[PDB]
Image (tube, rainbow over all chains, first blue to last red; front, side):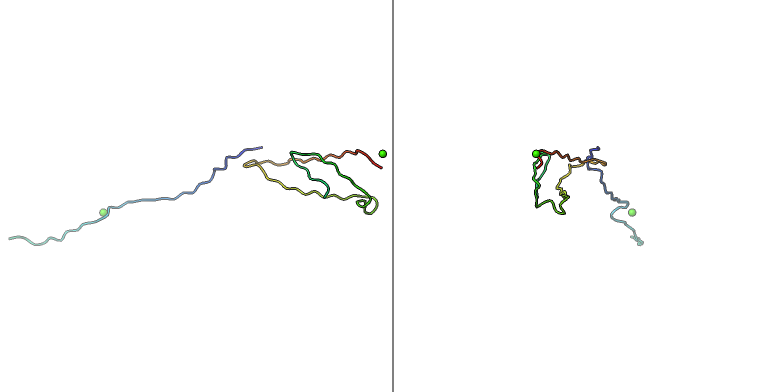
Length: 33
Length: 58
Ligand SMILES: [Ca+2]
Ligand SMILES: [Ca+2]
C-alpha cells in the first residue's frame, strides 16, 4: 500500500555562449608624410 | 444475468429453477467485473471474497 505523487519525470538540455559578436583586424599601412 | 454486485450494494438474492439445472446436476456461473482503480495507488496480493447462504430449498 504505497501512495505515489506521480511527478518523478525530468528531461534536460544545455546551452552556451563562448565568443564575442565581432572580431576586428587592422591593415593601416600608410603614413601621412 | 441474475444479479449485479457493487461496493455500495454488496448483497443480492437470486433464484435457480428447473431451466437452470442443465445436465440435471450442476449450475455454472461466470463473474464479470467492471472497475476503476484509485489514482497513484500501488499494491499486490489482494484477495476478493464472495459468500453464499441458502435461504430456502424445495
Ligand atoms: Ca573574439
Ligand atoms: Ca423447505
